[PDB]
Image (cartoon, one colour):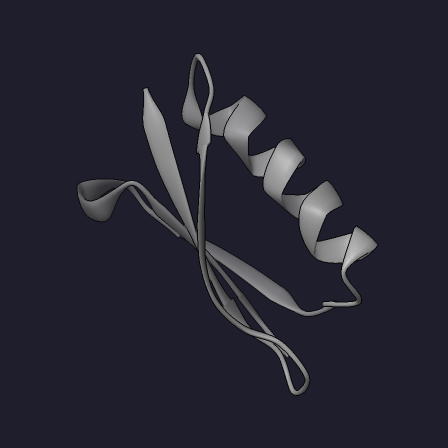
Amino acid sequence: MQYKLHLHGKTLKGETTTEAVDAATAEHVFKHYANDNGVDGEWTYDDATKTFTVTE
């Protein structure tokens, strides 16, 4: 299943996706991706849109 990530950092904004078995594991993948790209902030998830958000 596909899950989305919305990045809202001061130096990086946009969207990516990942294919994971469930949302909980998609979360950790995204959190790593955010971290490897210098985005550190508050995380929320919205199941209706299958979308994670990280905000700096």
